[PDB]
Length: 141
Image 1: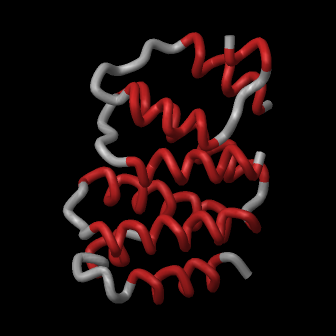
Image 2: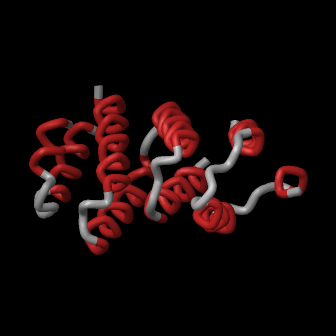
């Protein structure tokens, strides 16, 4: 994954890396999860252009449907940890988290999110994510 991260400076080969992820998919789950976490970190860096980040997020959302429950839960926990760290400055991570939540312990996940303290200057992005995936009657209150 580190080599792919180094090679994805231009952003042209990242799609080929996704094919490599497919080569991982058909050991595979852990490599895919690590690649997803590193891609989330790279998008959080913000160095990549808007179009490349949008295409990468779309491809990741499309590919996340086939992933198993354990990898999805691990990615959700990592996203919650990143939100607690408050190092997010783009809505692409919010869209990815919304897609992961839509794929679907979900009630416990949103309850734990509710118990947490929000980071100022990211409340609008949290609201964007919440309208992306609606909550229940009691959690929304």
